[PDB]
Length: 219
Length: 216
Image (cartoon, each protein chain N blue to C red):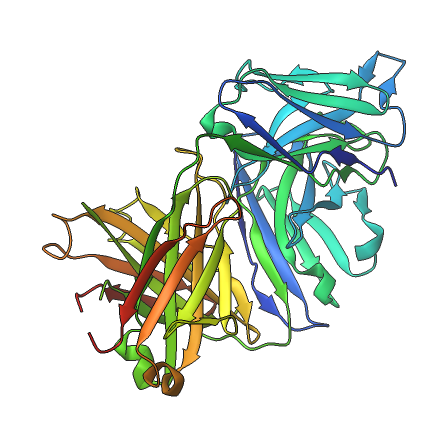
């Protein structure tokens, strides 16, 4: 059971700059009978099957752009992207086929760097449909921001609320390299009706100035 | 073109069975070995099984040996994975793939199927509740898809007419059910003068719901 270790777990680089991803195995994958290394690289974008980029450590699959270069030998291999493009956002996996069972590395996520961008914040009251059934989900979208670190805070009538909050992050957008985040405050209908103002706050550790969006149940 | 069309995934109880299918086209099927590779909820790829060109030799991951059976109908260009005595640890997205090179021993995979999801759980299939998200330059609308099981659901806007400015967020687990949301951002002149509908599908419950976003 050859262990394929991929370092680091995630990689961040600006558009146009060089990306180098490492993959460590446990045994030499070079065959001295024809001088070839038994290693392959795969690119997997969000929602898609893995796609073969490089086979035999350095042979590029027909159709892969020339900016993808594979190198290495023995137990240390490298995937180089000579100039990262917006579309290259993906998870990159190495795989050995020297001995059964074929094993894959845990993958290295490629993140793109770009200028800071404040989230576009939208807050939504519970729909009447949900309220009729006894529920009250207050939804807040924090869309198209950078960098990934962002902390949402919920306040009900001015007081912080932490119970009933569930958060969800998209993968980095392959067009503008931003992130988006969804935050749902799930309350009962009775508790939602017991208060008036609901506030979603987008904060980040580097600043004290949040981005605030609120609504009033009555107006 | 080479296409590997999978089918057969779904929800199944622990100890149950399920048969996955992989239909191939665009290459000489009998001249290639075929394989199954699964991917765990943490996006970890894992080879499962490989069958030779004529099926005389099969190879299995030790975790599935004696529980899964690989087979191929070379006349119908179809690959099968018969899974039995399923455990929760088998929950994963299952891919079929063509073992490249046509030779003995493992190799790399060039062509992958689109993947089918297998959920091993004793939880029951639950349809989602779909709620419109309307606001109380550009305007952001949404809809909330709450309390469904199992994965997946597909959310579109205006039947795929609105592709740009859409954010469909990954589902989270709440009370043994999944909940996700989706936002769409359109110009002010579009909404509310025009009609913005979120289309939600949950194939596991045969659920098909359209929710029109109406102003508050």
